[PDB]
Structure formats: C-alpha cells, structure tokens
Image (cartoon, rainbow, N blue to C red; front, side, top):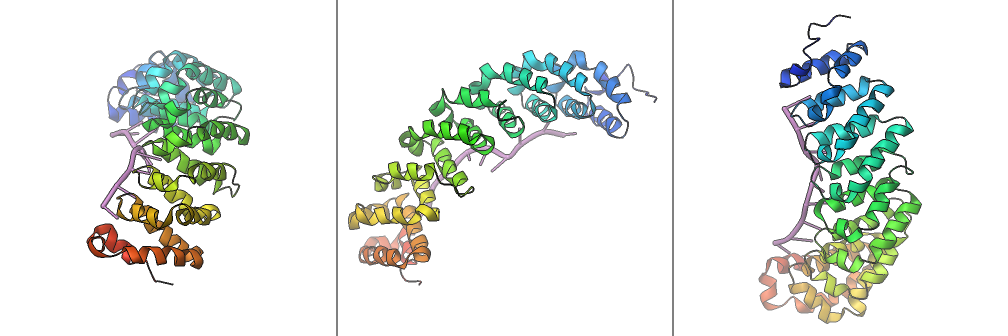
Length: 328
RNA sequence: UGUAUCAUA
C-alpha cells in the first residue's frame, strides 16, 4: 500500500536495475501498483516499449493491468505499431500485448492498425515476429487480414527470407478454408518456389503439415507437378531439398523413387550420381527404398552398381553411395 | 560433398 518510488517511476526505466525492480514490485504487489506504474508511464509507452529494458517492464505491466488499462494503452500504441514492430525491443512488448489481448476490441484495434503494414512487417527481422504472434494468438476470424494481405503478395513473401517463416505460421494456426486458399496460390508458384532459396522451405512445409495431420491434400498436388521433371529439380541446390522431402514422406516416397527409374533411367542416375546436390537425392532414394521397398532398392542398386566404377569411387559422394548397395 | 528462421535485460 506504500511506494518509495512513486513520482520517480519513469526514472526507474532508464536503467535496468529499475525495470527489474518494478517488475519485481508488480508480481508480488497486486494491482495497486499496476495502476501506479501504468498512470506514470502511459505518456511514455511507445518510448518504453522500444527501450533496452523498458520493453520488459511494459510486457510485465500488460499482464497485471486491467482490461480497460490495456484497451487504453493499446489505443496509445496503435498509431506507433509499425515503428514498434520494426524495433528489436518493441517487437517483444507488442507481441506480449497481442498475447494478453482479451476483449474483441483490443483485437479490432490491433488488426486494423497492422492491416496495411502486414506485408512490410513480415519481410522485417523483427516485424514478422509480430505478424507471427497474430496467428499464434488471435481468432481465425481476426488474423484473416494476414491471409488477405499475404494472398495478394504470395511469392513476394514466400521467396523472402523472413516472409516464409511467417507463412509457416499461416499453415499452423490458419483455417482449413484459409490454408486451402493460401496453398491454392502457393501451388501456382510451386515451380519458382521450389527453386527459390526460401520458397522451397515453404513447399517442404505444406507437405510437412499434411503429413502431421495425416490428411494429404496438396502433398499430391505438389508431387503431380514436381515429378514429371524430378531429375532436373534434383540436381539443384534448393530443389534437391524439396525432392528429399517428397522422398522422405511414405505416402509418396515410392511413386517418386518410381519416377527416377521410369523417366529417370540409368542416365538420370548418373546425373544424380555426379552432381553435388543430386548425389543426396540418389543417396536418400537408396536409404528409403531399402527400408520401404526391396523391389525398388533392387532396381535402384542394379543400376547404381554398374556406374560406381573408376574416378567416382574416389569422390566424397562416391564413397558414400558405395556404402548403400547391399545392406538388406 | 548441399538451404532459412527459431530472435531482446
């Protein structure tokens, strides 16, 4: 019921020892000191959220603070979200606010003031981690803005470094109607996303998720568009990782190994053999068929063995594939 | 022999 720091709360946020102090005097102290700290910081929220330590205190406050205090404190940050998102310290408190958000007003406020910055923030080191929180916390009805914002700039965000790490939380917390409209789009860029240094990490994710819900919708729509030309995407730094995934998911593993033999031929196996990225596709197609299908391992081996002769046997990828010929 | 991110005192 008594505070020695009253009238000097703001000066306790300029240094760290004070931020931990108030946080300490906020947990085991009740709401009495929640109205205290709030009232003497509200005029500095935006400033405190982006401080080296201020952010920590703001997050702490957001918890004990009552609804009305938040709704207020949100309407204060609302026109500063963008500069707070783009901030390494601000991105933290802004997320913590998106966490403690309860009422459906704090929601309509946050969504409205992020909506026209969605794309830009996702492409940001700290801006995306906030857009990731909206999916991780809000209702499907609420974070719909993200999906709407992201479904007009698919490749822009997917092929972008941090843009794809956000797409991964779309597929995680989205609606079966949403993800199955986001993927409708992604699928139309599966050519360029598989080759791209970041887009490929998303294609691997569409599959990853469906293989987690044991409900395969696009995993097949992917394979139907990535199989006809599988040797080409195999001898490629990034496409090779997408093909290893299809090769590592049972429900499709086989028919893909089966494309390396059908159209691939003893030729394609050579192309896989010598390439620095293909020799991993070939090397995986072995380990897998070996376990899943002894008629594939057998038809794979009776082509590989004839070609493991001479200079190859003395290469890094050569010695590795040699070890995978007869282990059944 | 070959890819991101997983991040504030």
